[PDB]
Amino acid sequence: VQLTAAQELMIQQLVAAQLQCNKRSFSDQPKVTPWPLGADPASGSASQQRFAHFTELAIISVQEIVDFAKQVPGFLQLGREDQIALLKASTIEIMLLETARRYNHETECITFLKDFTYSKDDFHRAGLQVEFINPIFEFSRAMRRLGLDDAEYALLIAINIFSADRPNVQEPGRVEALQQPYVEALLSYTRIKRPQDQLRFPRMLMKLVSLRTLSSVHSEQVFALRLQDKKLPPLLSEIWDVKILHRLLQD
Amino acid sequence: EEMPVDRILEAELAVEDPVTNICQAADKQLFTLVEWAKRIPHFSSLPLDDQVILLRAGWNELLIASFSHRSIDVRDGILLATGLHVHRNSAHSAGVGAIFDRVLTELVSKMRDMRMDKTELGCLRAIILFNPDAKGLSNPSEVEVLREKVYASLETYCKQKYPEQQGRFAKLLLRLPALRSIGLKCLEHLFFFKLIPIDTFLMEMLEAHKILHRLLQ
Ligand SMILES: COc1ncc(F)c(N2Cc3cn(-c4cccc(S(C)(=O)=O)c4)nc3[C@H]2C(C)C)n1
């Protein structure tokens, strides 16, 4: 019915935390291996470059995500091995939420960082397979249909992080306990924002279900990378089973 | 309601070596599950190819949900529809112990502690059934709309039967992600059993469909 002051401010904190994190990730734009232009040379090395480029983008996402989690009230009050178990499981999911957030239905394209725009086919040229690419864009479309604002996204991301059923979570009771106010806040916010649309809240929670499937489809993508001898950087290998992450938290 | 929870409750009530015993109980329940689906409002109004698709996509999470709730009063195990029990120790000797624990923790225990009633279960299963993301569907919007009516019936029921528990509706829905992951992992084990004493309807369900069609007519 009504939105507590503590709730208003937490949501503000979350929205703030996100924008701060995207401005830090834009710093890294000239850092990134450029995307090869013009016709590909016989050497084959434009493949390797596209794949390195995409991969460096993911890395930046992981960094952005860790910086974000650290700003989520409660997250740091958890044990360090739980922090990791939580960020491992949820990275791909959040990556997929962010991806959708950066999707444009009119160009059917996804914009990473400031102005790196990629089509379905760019995704294929960068080494990902259609069995993965299509679900990513189906998901983006579904997300667009929902029309989430910056607060709804931020909340849904926090809720996602505090999923007690991840592998190797040692204090699950605490994680559900942390999750619960964020779910409560989302209920209130959505019910005030759009009182005529009572279905917004459950629709949103059901995307958490979708993301479990997509996580799975993403494991299938990792399968195929090893089958093609595409090798992921250390941080991505660490996080998707193929030390560092600990360091990123410790900073 | 256009998705009346009473009718959904009626449908749940109208249906009353570890690895082998599980496949055997699964084959048994697939038959029952078709009769259960038929008694969910509007399921049978859908095109027949869509009824098939939805059951093919849902059966696994649907059987897990029901054997989980059925096991609420069992200690350190689950109760199969065959009437036979399965306990942690067995599950582990059979190399199925990790997923077994996850079921107990994330479903059986949670269901018990909430006293998840038979209507609330029914609604969750109807939500699982009516999955607009199942591939091949003639009209996915049709199915999304049915799913949504279950959202609405359910929340109302929760506010009316459990008004003092403001977080109840969401507590129920947040079982669904854990179920999905758990379900994917069980599908995996069922696929392995297939690559190595298996039955006929279950077999049909694991291939990429004549028994199912028959059964709905
Ligand atoms: C199978 O796993 C995998 N292998 C190789 C990849 F290149 C990859 N990428 C490349 C990427 C960038 N991001 C990504 C997501 C949000 C925001 C940004 S950002 C910070 O550049 O805006 C990048 N996510 C991925 C993932 C995938 C979901 C497309 N994933």
Image (cartoon, coloured by chain):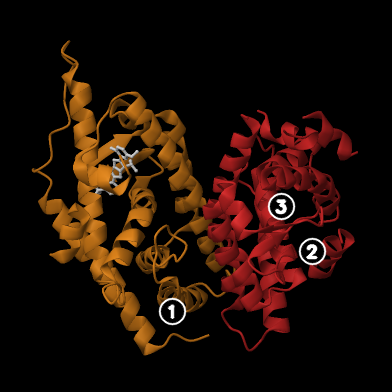
Chain colours: A orange, B red
Which label was assigned to residue A181? 1
Label 1 CB sits under 8 Å from any ligand 1 atom: no
Q: Residues within 10 Å of mark 1 (few under 14, many from 20)?
A: some
Q: Check disc 2 and report the residue beneath it.
A: B2
Q: CA distance from mark 3 to mark 1?
A: 31 Å
> Which residue occupies the foreground of this view, A251 or B91?
B91
Have a look at marks 2 and 3 and say if they share a chain: yes
First in sequence: mark 2 vs mark 3: 2
| Distance in Å between CA atoms under marks 2 and 3 | 25 Å
What's under tag 1, amino acid-wise? Pro
Chain ID of residue with mark 2:
B
Please state the quadrant of the image where ligand 1 appears. top left
Q: Chain of mark 1?
A: A
Amino acid marked by disc 3: Leu
Q: Indicate the position of residue A68 as horizontal and vertical percent values.
A: 25, 64
The residue at the far top in this view is A42
Residue found farthest to the left: A30
Q: Chain of mark 3?
A: B
Q: How far apart are the two marked residues, 2 and 1, measured between alpha carbons?
A: 32 Å
* Residue ID at (17%, 31%): A35
Residue under disc 3 on the same chain as residue under disc 1: no
**Nearer-the-camera pick, A217 or B112:** B112
Regarding mark 3 in the picture, which secondary structure is present there? helix
Describe the element under mark 1 as helix, strand or loop.
helix
For disc 3, the marked residue is: B63
Residue drawn at x 20%, y 39% as measured from the top left: A233
**Classed neighbour count for the residue bearing mark 2: other residues with Cα under 10 Å, few (<14), some (14–19), many (≥20):** few
Q: Position of residue B11 (x, y in %)?
A: 84, 60
* One can see residue A18 in this view: no
